Amino acid sequence: PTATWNMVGCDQNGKVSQQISNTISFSSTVTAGVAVEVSSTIEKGVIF
Amino acid sequence: AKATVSVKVTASLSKAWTNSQSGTTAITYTCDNYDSDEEFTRGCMWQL
């Protein structure tokens, strides 16, 4: 006996099965925006 | 007394690139029989 094995699950009273999954995904977003700012200020302002 | 009025216009354009990868494992266990070897038709499932 050469090989070594890892245990993945034990069931003393029935079936054991596994599913192994791999996902690879690529995504890209393009954003276009536009803003209008209309500010104003009142400042008064003599001796000191 | 001083008074100002400002008008600003902004325009933006971005582009994002995402890529990802995941892996998942899923083990499933079913209760099929009791220790006595009769078929399981009710009872409880236990985890060590």
Image: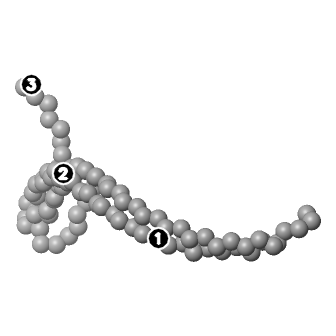
**Discs 2 and 3 share one subunit:** yes
What amino acid is labelled 2 in the image?
Answer: Ile
In this figure, which colouring scheme has been used for the structure? one colour
- Residue holding disc 1: A35
The secondary structure type at the circle numbered 3 is loop
Mark 1–mark 2 Cα distance, whole angstroms, equals 36 Å
**Mark 2, mark 3: which one is toward the viewer?**
2
- The spot of residue A23 in percent (x, y) is 17, 53
- The spot of residue B13 in percent (x, y) is 36, 60
Q: Which mark sits nearer the N-terminus, 3 or 1?
A: 3
Q: Nearer the viewer, residue B29 or B31?
A: B29
Looking at the rendered image, the quarter that the C terminus of chain A falls into is bottom right
- Residue holding disc 3: A2
Q: Is residue A17 above or below residue A35?
A: above
**Mark 1, mark 2: which one is toward the viewer?**
1
Mark 2–mark 3 Cα distance, whole angstroms, equals 35 Å
The secondary structure type at the circle numbered 2 is strand
The secondary structure type at the circle numbered 1 is strand
**Mark 3, mark 1: which one is toward the viewer?**
1
Q: Nearer the viewer, residue A23 or B30?
A: A23
Structural crowding at the residue carrying mark 2, measured as other residues with C-alpha within 10 Å and reported as few (<14), some (14–19) or many (≥20): few
Disc 2: which chain?
A: A
The label on residue B14 is: none
Residue at 10 percent across and 63 percent down: it is: B32
Do the residues under discs 1 and 2 have CB atoms within 8 angstroms?
no
- Horizontal side, residue A21 vs residue A41: left or right: left
Q: Seen from this angle, which residue lies furthest top?
A: A2
Structural crowding at the residue carrying mark 3, measured as other residues with C-alpha within 10 Å and reported as few (<14), some (14–19) or many (≥20): few
Q: Which mark sits nearer the N-terminus, 2 or 3?
A: 3
Disc 3: which chain?
A: A
Residue at 42 percent across and 69 percent down: it is: A34
Say whether residue B36 is visible: no
